[PDB]
Amino acid sequence: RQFGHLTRVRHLITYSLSPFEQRPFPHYFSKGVPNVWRRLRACILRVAPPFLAFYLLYTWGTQEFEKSKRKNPAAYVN
Amino acid sequence: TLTARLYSLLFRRTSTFALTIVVGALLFERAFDQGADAIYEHINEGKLWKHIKHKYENK
Amino acid sequence: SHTDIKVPNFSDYRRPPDDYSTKSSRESDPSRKGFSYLVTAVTTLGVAY
Amino acid sequence: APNIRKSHPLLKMINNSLIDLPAPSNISAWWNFGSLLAVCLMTQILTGLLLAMHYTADTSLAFSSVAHTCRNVQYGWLIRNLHANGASFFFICIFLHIGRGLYYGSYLYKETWNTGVILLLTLMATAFVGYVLPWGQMSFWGATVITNLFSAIPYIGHTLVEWAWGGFSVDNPTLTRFFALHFLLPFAIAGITIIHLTFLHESGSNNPLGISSDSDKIPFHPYYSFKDILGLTLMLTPFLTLALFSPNLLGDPENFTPANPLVTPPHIKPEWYFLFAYAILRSIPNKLGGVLALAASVLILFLIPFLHKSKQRTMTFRPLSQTLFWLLVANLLILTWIGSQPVEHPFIIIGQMASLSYFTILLILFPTIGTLENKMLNY
Amino acid sequence: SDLELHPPSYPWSHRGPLSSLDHTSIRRGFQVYKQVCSSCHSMDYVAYRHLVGVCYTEDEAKALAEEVEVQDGPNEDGEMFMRPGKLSDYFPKPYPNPEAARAANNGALPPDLSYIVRARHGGEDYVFSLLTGYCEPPTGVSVREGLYFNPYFPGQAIGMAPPIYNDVLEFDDGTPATMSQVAKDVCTFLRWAAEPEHDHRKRMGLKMLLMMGLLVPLVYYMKRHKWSVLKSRKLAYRPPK
Amino acid sequence: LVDPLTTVREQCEQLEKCVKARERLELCDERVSSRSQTEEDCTEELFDFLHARDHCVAHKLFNSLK
Amino acid sequence: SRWLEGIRKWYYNAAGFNKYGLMRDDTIYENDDVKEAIRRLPENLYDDRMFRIKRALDLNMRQQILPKEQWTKYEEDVPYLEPYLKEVIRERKEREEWDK
Ligand code: HEM
Ligand code: HEM
Ligand code: HEM
Ligand SMILES: CCCCCCCCO[C@@H]1O[C@H](CO)[C@@H](O)[C@H](O)[C@H]1O
């Protein structure tokens, strides 16, 4: 598929300025950084969980394995 | 007015641009190496052979 | 009717500080292109290395 | 014609695939991996070729030919490193590439997706047979254990392995055919990679919001060329940092000992990018089923397109399955772990559990949470 | 029991990402390799030639290869004969073949140290700990004839007897040759011997980091620049109603 | 001549963890050698001492080496 | 005990396809049915949807959403295609049947 036969579009007016008449990385604070946060706090509660969960299991696992090696002070009290 | 002088003289003509990408590179190389080496070597005084050399080449 | 249509404001919003009406955009932009191209000129440069 | 860039039989091919090519505007950064994957390939083939020019494929010269390449061949050390570490950059990317597709339903473009699975299989094989080449303890033992697996295949089994490699055991006659195979496959990857992009180009490129992009596409080049080159550097910098500061960070030391058939190392395990499956392999005890689990761990990808139920393509607006998805990656991540560990209690369990939670999330949860997710939208 | 003790972790002069090897120490190490290890441990991949320009002068190294004679190609009559080693010869092998060595070191086989530092988990940290670390076996544990207890070694029984005590050799640069100290240099040597690139590879890593630093922001600004035309764009729907 | 090692170990062997670990060790040592038929070894207890001693030996040893 | 109605509203706001300003129907994946369906859609609606969909791609392109005010409220979402999409599907099942 090429250009000129994608869709039946009507009544949309767009306005844009040359790259040289504007700023590249504008308003890092006014709108920039906020949205970055507007995002970290939007998925953290959806992504983090299973990862955190994984972690606990990784730890439990390693710790347990590393315990089942050491001897029990009482396997021989005689 | 560097930037403006720059554009007019160096960045306007496709020809001029390329030509300063080269002369610009030669100069960048020479300067960027020395500088890096320097920074490198200095963070390692008395460890490099270039430093220990004299002891055995006489000194 | 189209006469009823204006171009929104990019003033401040996006325009770099040398762009606000009643002042020729042209005296200030050979300087604006100079910067940009300089950044690009530098990349081609760094890349060659 | 005027343009003379849209008329020429060859340029027209380029100006229609890297310029003037209609790409959606809202393409996410996840789409930067096809690019990377491709350049990742150019890179391997290069460094490899250049590295093959100093290698000898013979039990008695392999290990040292490589060593010599590193100690004698100018910048040889760097080339080897890049190639080795590159293998990983390659898989990390191919894995993020799969991902993006799995969760933007890119896979609904069946043909372009099926070839992609063939790309993964191929890229694997070439990387398995390629690690033997240096002929170190793991190279050898890995080859001997992993190849011998086919042995489970009843009847026409032993005879396959027994022919696959040299004659009776991973020895010279197999290092050669492996070297050859390694040299050949990458070019087949590139070949197929063309078919991949062909099928792709048939339809547009999918996008994050999963709804028709026709509404407003943008010329690839002016934009995406830049976009990808940016990605190239942003991802290539860690590659090099790793490649130049901790060269062996991801490499088994045991593979610095020339192969020796009288010393089987403890903990024989394939490269990390294979572990997840190595895990699911030793999950089921019955040697046969084990292979099948292994085979299915990857081949399942062919089924994904038939397990899509959502009335929506991507899963941007599908919070439920969204956690299911991450719950899944986490799962693979765990399988990886379990694979690097010995076959002992704390693990053995976590292993077959995770392994089980793998096939369920793909086979049964996803599709189910799928429809259920539809009812909730009144559909 | 698959129970083991793991080496600590010393601040080697060459662990910094930007810090190279201390060649003065490398030089030393070479000496302890040559004067003590080289009688059991082969180092097939390094050769005198390498010392040149790194921790020894050309002539200095030339004279150091002379000290050893090597077996060389057929006569005019076809037989093996000896001769003073040149600069191009690789470090001598202590034994004609493995089995030959296994029989000289009571069964065990002293590994070639060319890549040792990277053939064992821990690298120098490991080797060091191992060298300066033998001691009597703990209670209940008994090592057999010919083996020597060393906790740091898996199985805690090494076929290798403590190879390094105070003095044993005398660093000529004028350095207090204490076991601990001597073992340090030997380790920094083993490092170099395993990856001579090291210093080169890092100075390089520096230069790469600075390029990434400079290159990405440029292309970032460039990417941001072309795009702006969209990021800033403004739609509007105007049906004639 | 005196090896800085042995000096910096004497100090370390006095730090809490060490002293606390040396003890838990000497006990097992004198207990395993006291019976005639026991399977216990004092390897574990020993390592803990070494994993502790050495850890600080490292934090300082190299300060004295050239 | 727990209204599907309570739920549906939960999910709607959960999904979030409204923060972009588009109706539920503006997201249904365009398989064969939805394609026929949309083609039957009156022109009023077609252009309406067209703009919405583009306004969404643009937000998404900018990594920015629509201000809270403009978020389409659950109870005001207009199922503009479902009626059509429905006939399409039963029109088809009729044929999928006859041809047997
Ligand atoms: C010289 C100071 C010296 C070094 C250095 C050294 C190192 C070394 C290492 C790291 C090993 C490998 C340990 C492992 O297998 O993980 C090792 C092993 C043996 N060595 Fe050694 N060794 C040094 C010197 C000597 C000397 C002088 C001899 C011979 C008299 C010798 C011998 C051996 C032997 C035998 C082994 C045992 C291997 C085993 O499996 O038991 N070493 N050495
Ligand atoms: C080495 C092999 C591969 C290379 C070089 C490669 C290359 C590409 C390229 C150039 C793109 C375009 C940009 C993008 O959408 O990311 C692409 C798209 C795609 N690839 Fe691959 N690919 C490879 C492997 C795979 C694999 C393993 C799969 C399948 C599991 C796959 C699935 C896809 C699909 C579905 C698209 C994306 C469509 C979209 O969402 O827009 N590719 N691939
Ligand atoms: C598809 C891209 C490729 C992948 C995935 C790949 C992967 C690998 C792997 C895993 C290694 C092992 C590195 C190590 O020893 O740790 C390797 C080695 C090797 N590859 Fe490739 N390779 C690829 C392409 C090539 C090609 C096409 C050539 C050259 C024609 C090549 C030639 C070699 C050689 C000679 C070695 C042995 C030298 C060495 O291992 O250092 N490789 N490759
Ligand atoms: C993509 C960024 C690439 C960074 C450029 C790589 C720089 C490699 O530069 C290398 O530095 C060494 C140390 O001085 C020199 O000995 C080599 O001759 C030189 O090629």
Image (cartoon, coloured by chain):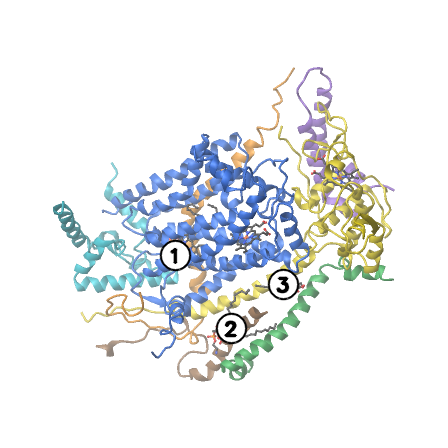
Picture colour for chain F: purple
Tell which chain the image draws in blue. D
Q: Within 10 Å of the Cα at label 1, are there few (<14), some (14-19), or many (20+) other Cα atoms?
A: many
The chain drawn cyan is chain what? G
Q: Is residue B32 above or below residue D360?
A: below
Q: Any atom of ligand 4 within 8 Å of the CB at mark 3?
A: yes
Q: Which mark is residue C40?
A: 2
Exactly how many numbered labels are in the figure? 3
In the rendering, what colour is chain B? green
CA separation in Å, label 2 and label 3: 21 Å
Mark 3 residue type: Lys
The local crowd at label 3, few if under 14, some if 14 to 19, many if 20 or more residues have their Cα within 10 Å, is: some
Query: Which chain is in yellow here?
Result: E
- Residue denoted by label 3: E207
Chain letter of the orange region: A
The residue carrying mark 1 is D196
Can you say whether E139 is above or below D213 in the image?
above
Report the residue at 64% width, 56% height from top.
D77
Question: Residue D220: image x %, image y %?
Answer: 39, 67
Q: Nearer the viewer, residue F33 or D124?
A: D124
Tell me if G44 is positioned left or right of D306 in this view: left
Q: Specify whether E87 is left or right of D153.
A: right
Q: Quadrant of ligand 2?
A: bottom left
Cβ(mark 1) to ligand 2 < 8 Å? yes
Dot 1 and dot 3 residues touching (CB under 8 Å) = no
